[PDB]
Image 1: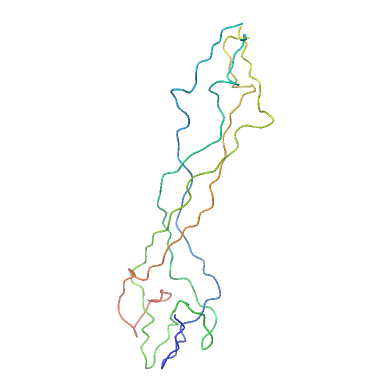
Image 2: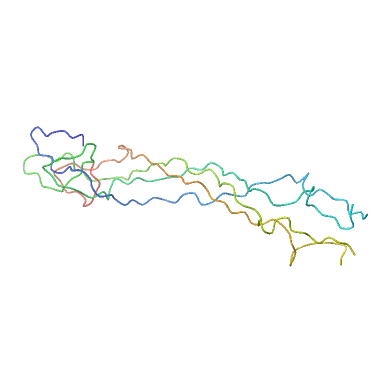
Length: 52
Length: 105
Length: 53
């Protein structure tokens, strides 16, 4: 509706909306996937265990 | 040096700020044009841009060209969504710098 | 004591399971006026509760 005045006919089937209409949507994102952290080559560097 | 060693000050330890990324995905949202119902009354003031509907009236002389029966549904594609999670806390502050037993036999 | 050290059953170690949340996102969809098809004409039998077209 463009708020046009009916020249001859009566547009009684069109009216403004005052109450919201509930709509159903589909599924969405759930969670992220596995990602790599750190470098295996430099990770877990060996430490000297020699006593004093 | 010491008899017992560990990785606390300088070593490849664990615990850090978690960071991750999510691959781009398409989310579909369907905006149904039905179930809007009817509000207000007729023969009065109506707001602009109002969706026009039909009252199922039998036209005595005129033709109701604004009322029709739907034959096929409308499928729409929604926009993008969230990217990834934010920073999270790792480890417990009161238990921070906890000593680890590493003395040898 | 033991030559090899580890903290599994009971020990003061570090590291835990991180917990995080994603920022709120809203899905926007455009209701296209086309692609709805059409069957029959007007003045005629019409399905109840059908979307006006």
